Length: 63
Length: 51
Image 1 (cartoon, helix red, strand yellow):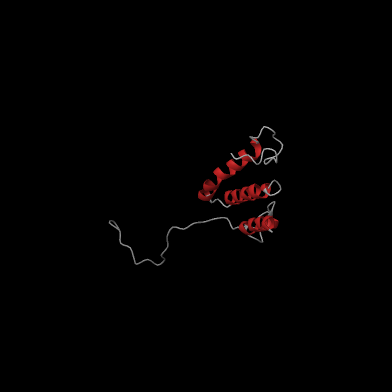
Image 2: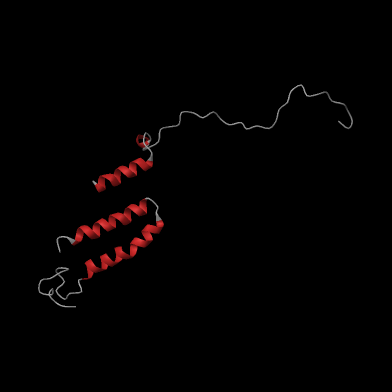
């Protein structure tokens, strides 16, 4: 899962950049919120460890 | 015409626009992109990214 997360976020960022350059404002607006959510998710590490997005020790928690 | 009498016009004309003849424009920096439209260049960039 860790190896597979960066491609998703970066490819969505590519989508956002493309729609910016093409001047397609509506789609860019629809896509910015997910961009920021992914940014927050990747750069917060709510887990106290703060070394991996998914941590085997923190994983297996029901919440 | 109120004080003299004219003939039918021997030459009809009207207002027109005079400009300086377009010259060979001094080549612009980045004139090497002119053979292809900007949209082609951007599609090239993003096709490179996608490939």
